Image (cartoon, rainbow, N blue to C red):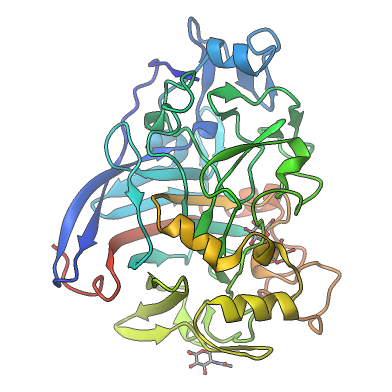
Length: 434
Ligand SMILES: OC[C@H]1O[C@@H](O[C@H]2[C@H](O)[C@@H](O)[C@H](O)O[C@@H]2CO)[C@H](O)[C@@H](O)[C@@H]1O
Ligand SMILES: *[C@@H]1O[C@H](CO)[C@@H](O)[C@H](O)[C@H]1NC(C)=O
């Protein structure tokens, strides 16, 4: 797709810290850009929509190639249309914003410049950030993660994509998302199936896969840390159901692991660690600091800080595994106790190390789940399972919670705030910022 300028594209600024082993942290200046799927897509020579509701213009978009040549992406009014605002080192995203249209959530990327994505090499480093999840009830997910996206949004590989990173193109993740309107410089109109439960989305014949590091997926009830390997580290297109993931009939038929080696404290047995109120170790009605460390062995460590007190990831006992570190032993034990083979089939942490050794793009979003109502995160799932089944209970939300239409009308004012992002070698982000 190309880019049009009926609406100016001004990326909201966002500062973060880059720290060194020497003990100092220096301020960096970046900005955020909203994903292409959220933008107005119209004809290059007029205001005629190429996509409206959940269907494509059959004349402007008779196929993927022609559609890409005839259509462009436009600018976004971040605050008034998407409810996305920043202030210094802080970023806030509102759940539902009502303007000339109704908007739900947003997916944003951190930029190095006005035309490129900031890449982060996680291996050997740690990532810290503060978060306020107090306004996120059951069914919502304020996410912060990394994906192996190209820094230019794909422009160099796909010449027909001239909008690039400036317009948020090139997304990919371990679900090999088929809901993307533009993949590899082409539209996704061929094989498009509108959603039976969502008036603004659909499923195309193509998906976009790549490694994904889910550092933070949570609401005020539950939180999870999950690495997802793919046999092909970087962004790569897939065909229909061969994609696997959430948008396909066969979830495990693709090249990526849609489940991952997840770590949710509640699911592991500690139901008193994270929750709303002073009865939990970490009170989700108050802001907290989350630190994630990627050691060279390929294992992942985690600690939290709230009101000056530090808490390491709680100890978990799963099979012959005991500890608080996400490593090969934990992931093997989880597959044994909870079931599954997706993570190990895709190479596990060894294959995942290939992704963290390379560049990854930072993504921040707020979303509701039209496929599983976020039950996999904060409730009992599958809903037919009981508490006797190992790993079924992931949170205290009712199995009837998370219906999109319901949460959108009952909690329109929900929101999430990410702030004070710090990155640098292991053991350095706790030092004085600059
Ligand atoms: O596809 C939705 C959601 O799935 C998450 O994986 C679940 C999986 O769906 C479930 O069958 C299994 O029992 O548990 C895993 C871990 O919670 C996946 O981690 C999410 O990224 C994804 O959005
Ligand atoms: C949960 O984790 C916290 C912090 O590690 C710990 O203090 C508490 O005792 C744990 N509770 C249970 C029931 O395991």
